[PDB]
Image (cartoon, rainbow over the protein chains, first blue to last red):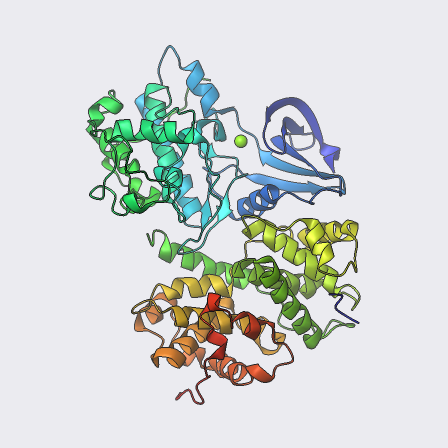
Length: 5
Length: 297
Length: 258
Ligand SMILES: [Mg+2]
């Protein structure tokens, strides 16, 4: 998962 | 950065491979360089080097090889080690016709046990003590080297890699597949090395895992629940193992005196819990009259 | 064999002080905050469950991140890159079988490239100057567990649980040493379960008394009461599994009588 969106 | 070292010769090969004797041009100091290749596109810096470097930074002791420095580029990792005359194995070979003098052995063992006790008291396990990984200088020192296979451990231990220790020096608990092993494994290796310093040949030179067990059983006698509570419940123990009478230490390493033999049996105990610790072993009467003689190189 | 038991504990105590991150690092960080770090640790916990990594590994990775962030400014867009290499490093140190670099790339949905993960790895080693063998909460707890009468699996698992919750919250747990947090957690677990106290034998071992632990315990106790409402829930979930004797379902004690 991409975290800082 | 390699600016100051002049290579001299290659002096060995390990798992990162190439090892050079080199000289600091400005200080004069003679170093050993382990050269680790990276080329991004692999799995980065090998776990063995991570461990070797991080553990040796903590282990500052006269009987442990000193990591002097770590030098980077984005393409090469260099490990600058203190440099040392010979490995123990090349020495046993040269003593072919003279033997090795007992106070040289006694001194060596005692020093080995010191450096080993320092490791164990800093929660580091060596896991590959053998004569090729033990280096000797002209002033009479001997030092643990090659922390390639070493690892930080916990109290109490958990499961760590099984595929462990050069066969000849591997402890029976590892061969019998025990899920838990500790400091006692390194002791088993020095015991073997002790015997080997006396006779100048390997105590247990097996060819496979089972060969090695049975060599060990043939000398020390096959273990039962008396000698080693819990043996028979071990993953790789088989009720069909041949049952051999224990001998008779006076015959395992005949030139050894009483203190000698007492020590080795304490080091070669089946039960990792009865097996003597490096700390304790330094107090043994084998060492009463010990000194630190130079050898002949 | 508690073979070098005292010696090691003594050595861990000395090292925990030198391996301690700066307590204020987050004030000096311009583009990140405590809750963003909470979000990263939470995610690292899921990564550990996904990849079946040791607890020691997760605890180690966290120590790296905090130490690395104690000296290097990082942007929101990169906090996770740092987070991934920290874990890769943790695994290589600690795990019989570390996941491949690719796996660490994959668990970001490919935010960063392999090339960047290895470059961060290198950069992380540089900044830590390779000091990776850091004492952790999990290392103290495990020794303390040797002092229970007798061994209680719930006590252990629930101690791991609380020890683990402290990773998540910089404020306040960055100001408590690993050995103290483990003190708080062990005592807190024991009391919850069996109703009993920090044993006199660990007062002898560690020099900590209920009194010395009170402050960290006060914090740990709140963290526990408020657990089920925390924005981060990966530890709690993790600790529902049979693997941990479902300890995250037990009720926190409503008072500590201190
Ligand atoms: Mg070597």
